[PDB]
Length: 99
Length: 99
Image (cartoon, rainbow over all chains, first blue to last red):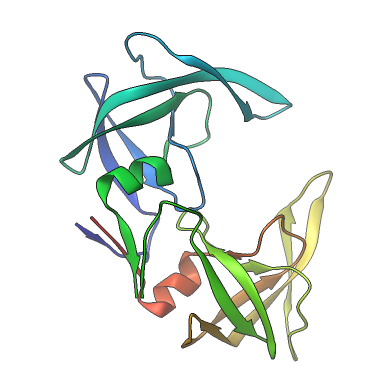
């Protein structure tokens, strides 16, 4: 789709057999989604949380569907004020900024 | 232009007769630029900072040129880890996310 920027650019996300929503955030390198369970092996990852560093999980090679478009990418599972789709997954979508 | 998302989407910004760069950040409502002087009137603005509420300046009706495109918009002048072009100004440029 074409997403205008007149409001926060939230998108429907299907991941881990669940439907949620997340913000398309070109200011974020990584994708972070809270309160979803993902299968298999993860790697430790540090994010800045409320208070200090939080130790959370990074899952690789995860199928994600964003507004109906299927990609595979890395997802951080951890506390976040809002779910965020970062540039890692947007680049897998072939997403571009245009003006 | 068309900007891909494999790397941080920085753009050249001409504002207050100065040249700087800033990050196109669809996760940010407001545009915030450090260490520029803007002419005339601003309205006092409070933002969350490290340690404080930070008292910064909101300037309205500021000419800004981004990758050579000329718009008018609102700019917050205040401390920021990276200069950010938010959705307010991206909406003035007519920027869209596309995939």
